[PDB]
Image (tube, coloured by chain):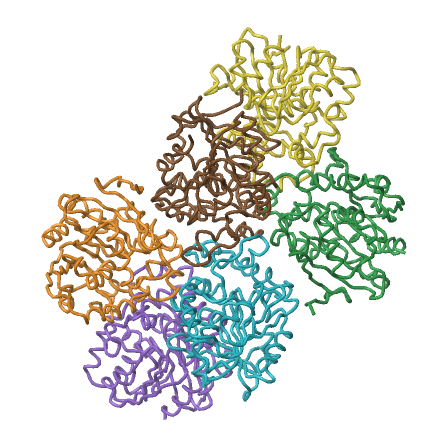
Chain colours: A yellow, B green, C brown, D cyan, E orange, F purple
Amino acid sequence: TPYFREDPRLTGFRHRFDTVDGVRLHFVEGGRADGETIVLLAGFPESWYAWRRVMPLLADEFRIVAPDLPGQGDSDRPLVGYDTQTVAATLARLLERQNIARFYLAAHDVGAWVAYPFAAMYPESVKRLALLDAGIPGVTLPAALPIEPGNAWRTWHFAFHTVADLPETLIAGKEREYLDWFLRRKAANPESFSDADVDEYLRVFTRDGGLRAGLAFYRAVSESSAQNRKLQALGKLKMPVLAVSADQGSIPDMAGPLEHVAEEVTAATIAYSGHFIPEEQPQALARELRDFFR
Amino acid sequence: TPYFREDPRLTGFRHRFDTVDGVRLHFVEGGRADGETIVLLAGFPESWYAWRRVMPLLADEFRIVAPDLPGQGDSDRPLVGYDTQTVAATLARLLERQNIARFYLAAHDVGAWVAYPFAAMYPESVKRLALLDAGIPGVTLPAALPIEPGNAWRTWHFAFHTVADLPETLIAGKEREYLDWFLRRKAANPESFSDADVDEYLRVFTRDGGLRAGLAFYRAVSESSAQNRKLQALGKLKMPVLAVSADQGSIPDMAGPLEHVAEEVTAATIAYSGHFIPEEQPQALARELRDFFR
Amino acid sequence: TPYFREDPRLTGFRHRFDTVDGVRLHFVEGGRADGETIVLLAGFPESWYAWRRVMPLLADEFRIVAPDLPGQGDSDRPLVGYDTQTVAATLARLLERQNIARFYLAAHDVGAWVAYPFAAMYPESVKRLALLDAGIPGVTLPAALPIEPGNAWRTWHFAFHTVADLPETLIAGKEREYLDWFLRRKAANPESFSDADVDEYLRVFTRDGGLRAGLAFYRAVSESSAQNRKLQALGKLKMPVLAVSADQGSIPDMAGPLEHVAEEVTAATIAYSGHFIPEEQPQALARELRDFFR
Amino acid sequence: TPYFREDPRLTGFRHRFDTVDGVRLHFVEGGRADGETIVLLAGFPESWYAWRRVMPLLADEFRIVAPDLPGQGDSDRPLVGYDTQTVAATLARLLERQNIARFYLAAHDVGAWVAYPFAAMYPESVKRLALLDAGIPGVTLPAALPIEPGNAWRTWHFAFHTVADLPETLIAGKEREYLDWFLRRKAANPESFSDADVDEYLRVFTRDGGLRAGLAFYRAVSESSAQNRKLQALGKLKMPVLAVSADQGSIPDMAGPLEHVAEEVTAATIAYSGHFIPEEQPQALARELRDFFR
Amino acid sequence: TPYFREDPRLTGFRHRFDTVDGVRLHFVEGGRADGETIVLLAGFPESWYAWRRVMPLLADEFRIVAPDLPGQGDSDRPLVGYDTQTVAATLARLLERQNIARFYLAAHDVGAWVAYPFAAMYPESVKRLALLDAGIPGVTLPAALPIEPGNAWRTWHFAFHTVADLPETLIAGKEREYLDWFLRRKAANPESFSDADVDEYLRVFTRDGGLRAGLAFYRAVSESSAQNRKLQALGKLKMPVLAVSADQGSIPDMAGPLEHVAEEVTAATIAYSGHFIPEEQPQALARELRDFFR
Amino acid sequence: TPYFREDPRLTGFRHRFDTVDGVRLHFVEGGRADGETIVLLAGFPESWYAWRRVMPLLADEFRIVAPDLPGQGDSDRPLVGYDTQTVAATLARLLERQNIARFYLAAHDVGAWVAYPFAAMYPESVKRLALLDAGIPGVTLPAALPIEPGNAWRTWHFAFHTVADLPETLIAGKEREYLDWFLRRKAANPESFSDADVDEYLRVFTRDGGLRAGLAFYRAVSESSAQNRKLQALGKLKMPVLAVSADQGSIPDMAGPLEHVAEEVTAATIAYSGHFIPEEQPQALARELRDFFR
């Protein structure tokens, strides 16, 4: 038996590791043993931990799997392979090895970057797709982003992260301030993140290669964009897509651009939420997901 | 007589200060006493010093005035007023007290941001206008800027600079690294800047309020942008305009968008030059200005 | 439902955030659900927390809302808008969004600076006004302040705070010493502030932009003064005004100068109190407010 | 013979020390040996060195003595005695020991605070008096000073310096930043002070008891004010008084207020000068002094 | 009602502050409400806290008032006035404001410096006087002090403290070492001071102006001596005076020299005690004071 | 021949070392090869270097030997033996090994402490004795030294140095400040010590065991005193003694008390000099020594 550990708080959820062609991946699994499976993907600068408030609310009805993608949380941080097709194929191999054959997929922020090529490459495993307050490189994320005061703070980090070496130079010694700004400035209510939450995100941020790996997603975005444009030309996604917005989120209109990549788009807006919907309005989000994942 | 000081290197040029409504401005003046006047404006993260290699080349024929704008170099750094109309009016006042009634105007980078409303507001004062490798807020600077790796590094700083407090936090203790990145990464040949050149820019960067004032221009960009849009609607620019591009500059096409704002646009591209045309190709730029300023 | 959090100490009071035209504001609300409403404003270098000892004494009978103004406590710190007309308009928008249409207003220190243009601009929303130990820019705060050693310490900070860049330079690394001096030297009994109290004020003083925002109120005092003198010429305040001074406070006579801006001015002096009346004599002040707010 | 040292730059001027009732005082003396004597007094945060540009211009005609007052430059720093009557009496004793019985007196800044009670107590020794850009405590210096941003930076330091212990706490580790602000922000042209000039003022500023003694003059101001009114009520000054203003100086009108303390007041304004007239416009000032000291 | 706080350890004693002509003074009061009053004064480097072990032992019989003198403990630290006649007058004003008209006075170390001019100036208010291990400047304190190694350590700090600026320079960064030496080296048993006791003395030693004000008493000693010689020429003290020695104290003979200044001198020596009698032998000292103040 | 080095500035003087019963002593020798010999002794906190300005003035006529005593300058610092009889014996052994049998002796400060038992023990070897501004332990140095603020700064260090361990603790890291105070505060003109002079004394002060050995002289003063009382009881010094005072020196009357220890005493006062006569008035001192040392 492989070693696993029960979460000290999420009763019934276990921390596991699995090594997938040399890449060790951390994931948390639990929930209803006989239920349909939900797979949850998080983004920057977070990890599986972002779903920690939604997971126990859905556990009564669903089987729940929340992995740390390569370069996230406690998973390994390879040197290359942060184009989203490679990340999705690695996720597919992790799920295959855990005998997760078909599931609902909900993905937030950069996690949604991974979810689009995943759904496009393995449509047979994704029964329904929910994308939360995020653009998709090359198909819905615009090639240019606003610079006018009032909106720039929402997207300034995109272009910054693509610059070589300078982000590492400026963030050094200022890691907690950088994280603190990202999390608390984009929430509707900053108290949605405790000091203990920031501590946890700082742990995986400053841990060997965390910053390098986080930036690598942005630095591979032009390759990921070209991949998605090739995939989009094969046809729109056929499975139902839920475009989940937040009334104070980063994306003004989620459903509109997604109608160009999916045949059936259902729109939902979460009230009283900034960008971090799974942590800010877990109940409201759980409700939409449970209702859509049917 | 006010105190003035001869430049230890630019023979015939003198450093002066004048106080304009409580605001002291540093400027360097020289050249042919009987000549037609050229006024030279520089941008971020520089000062009058950016023109130090062009100024002696034109001194034989023209009378040259190179001021530090408010918030630049050795000029004072007021707390507000960095919308470009207020900066332009402050500049106009300085020129009046120096009995500069009519002149040619060449402006680089954020200096060019000031040059557009100045020429729009004081049409008679500006004989001819040269704008060098810069967008003008709200009229030639697009409302959205590239995020593709490969072009995003040219413009990422716009949105970053608009964010409150985070830039001061990240730049602290890394002022030289930040400045060095701007100068050497955006030049075609980084040896266009000696270590002594960087030392001089660092001196004015780190002096009392240097960073604050530099950031203040970007943080006021929505207001300048609206101001420029308002004057935009009042007619095209009166006087002839030379749109100077650099083949490796920040702006792909300078002449094109300026045709939307001026009656007579003359196009010029400086070869083998990055963003810092006055320092990278002084001789070629001086010739273009010498021929256009007739 | 928005996320809110009960105060662990002020039982029956909840911490909330609301976003007003891009600016997120923190506020604490509680008290008797069917009572009349009192709105409480604090000044420098404090926050809503300065009312923490008065709030439970009035909660039996009044509805109580204590917001952090823009630039205070846990509210956002915009880059501009610290002229008190803009701040009062922002506060008005915040109150409207909570359907607080008519209320009693009590304001201390810089809080009173915002309270005056608020009462002048929205007289129908302010049933009665209480101003605590403060002058009002341009109408009751004198244009010159004392320099004699026995009095100069009460007002020296005013002019200091208007200087660009030097205050940030001198306070850096001495934030606690600066805070400690203000709170404990201006109270009649320095033990009115515990170490945990200073810790709390130090937390919000040192958070992103805390010093910048606190200083911005003083740096905009000339615009705030010009605004108030225009409002004063439209007529004096129409609602009853309570001028509360402290026998050891900063202002020798509150009622006197205020008779020129309000029609019915009632005077009260709290004994055994320095400048921080709500923290130094909370019952005495609660009695005066309870009696006046009828 | 006592040890003395020739100034390496001021030809004909010697640095001397003399002990005056336990207090060692440094002074620079030179100029025409049989000429009439000018005594030069400087203020905060300077020393005899502030007169270094005027002294050689007048040395042809006058014997010139430039002392460091107690608490200034290289003179001792007693613990008490910074009320200006005691400082003036100490200066008288120094001059008596150097056989200087009658002289012209020119005094700048806090030096002028010493000059007024000196002139009032020893009228037979002061042939004529020149006061430069300074108010005199209790007589021409107002009891309250302006606070509008625009003129507040000119006088903010007065009240600050009267505060016990906080100025030492805030200035510690920022001595050069504090000095640099005072000298360069208050001059019409900041290049009137070289780096080596700031270095010299920093040397005497950071030397044992330097800050304590400089601040002590402001802290004794109320005693100094009371002394001066006792003298000012005993009759106007008898000798001619030259009130020297600067067009960009700290004080709007010098001659006006001085007409109440002296029978014969002559007005002079030095053009293109900030507060530091002896360093900023030495030739113009020397001409005014030579012309008046007649 | 003024704010007061019960001492967490001393039953029946309250911490208070009162403002006396601008100077806020901290004091601890308690004991038998209708009992006769004892006022207790401490010296360097201590505070009211030095009496904390004697105070409960006398509280059954006497009303007890233990103030921090100006410059001590949590009392304000004015800039000047540490000549002991001025301190005594400040103490007198504090006692009058508390309606303490006639009382017993027991004073230790520099506190005894204050008590002698107090009793000479206000003989009707001092029923009886106890002076503990201290000389009186100019009157019992010798003009020269020992240099022999075996005893010079008892008094070396006297002359050291009068030196300007050098003490601050040497003690900086060594405050705890300096205090520890004073308290523990002069006690007969160094365990008379716990680490928590040293912590408390360090807190008030290192607070704003603590070292400055502590030294000021010694720096004004020649003014205090001249004052005491004038007072002594008016006649010897008429009330009974108790001269309290310690067998290992700083002063070899208390009673001898005091017979020249007081008419009735009672001698007492406390055994097994160093200089800090109130803390080292509280019960023996309390019995002597009780027997003498009855 | 032993290695010796010529002094780089004092031409004709050589630096030498010799070992005396395990203790290396550094000394400088030069002057008239066939002249009579003067041995020169310096004190705290100096070395032979204190005589560098006197040595060349006498070198034309006299043979001059200026040693570093044990614990001074570049000589060894033994662990014990700082009673002045042991030091004098160590000096005697050095002079014998260099075949200096009879000579004039001039001694300053602690050097004079050594000169007295030397002259008392080896009278045939000392032709004449000159003592410069110093008392002699137990015979001329009083057992108590004055503590008026006006005079305590001259002698406070005696008692301080006798305290175990605290001087090392307080002086650590402040060696230059401590030296600077000693040298420049006791000179009539502090410019008698250059920064290079202070550098030289700081070098030997800070050299390993420098502070320990310097303090050891003061810590042994009581043994030295008892030795000196025994020797004096054997008779007055029989050779002529010159008592050299300074008009601003440490010792008010030198010749007076010396009349009790020597048979014939000549008095001389050097004008315009603080304590450090050899450095402050080298020419005046050279003339007096010259006239007496015949």
Q: Is residue B120 left or right of residue A11?
A: right
Which is nearer the eye, B198 or B85? B85
| Coordinates of residue C11 in the picture (x, y in percent) | 40, 26
Residue F222 drawn above or below residue F174: below
| Coordinates of residue E120 in the picture (x, y in percent) | 19, 64
Q: Quadrant of the N terminus of chain E?
A: top left
Q: Quadrant of residue D186?
A: bottom right
Look at the image and tell me whether residue E150 can be seen.
no
| Coordinates of residue C148 in the picture (x, y in percent) | 43, 59
Q: Is residue F50 left or right of residue F80?
A: right
Residue F292 drawn above or below residue D291: below
Look at the image and tell me whether residue B33 can be seen.
yes
Residue A278 drawn above or below residue F139: above
Residue lying furthest top: A34
Query: Which residue is depicted at the point 16% across and 44% down?
Result: E59
Residue E190 drawn above or below residue D74: above
| Coordinates of residue C54 in the picture (x, y in percent) | 39, 34
Which is nearer the eye, E285 or F161? E285
Q: Quadrant of residue A61?
A: top right
Q: Quadrant of residue C216?
A: top right
